[PDB]
Length: 151
Image (cartoon, rainbow, N blue to C red; front, side, top):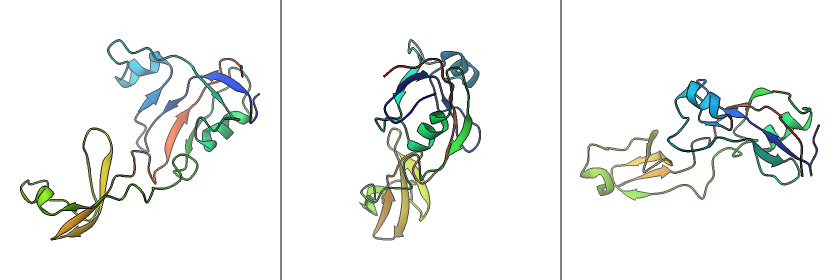
């Protein structure tokens, strides 16, 4: 039971359109996904439906969830990162890869550490690697789980 202005310590297990746990507050699941991390400590994330903390979508899947509830739904890239961003559209010189089999293609997705570059342009002169994001223009699961309520 929360609203736009109520905090709640819930542990969601955001996954991928493939069911791959990418983010989880429950350290347990972390081990079930092989992401428990080294020393990292997966604790309950206290979000506030009235702070825009988490993506609305999820913020809504909890809006109607008491303390202890669980809603493993997939938020649409529209509610999550709201489709892809335009300010994430990069454009490197063909050379930026010409000297590397990296040969970008009009649909590539290479990251430099985590942020992929959706190469929407494959001009033999350059490529438009739309950085975007991992959940950019993509929907991801959310195995939320209310554990408490705060603010």
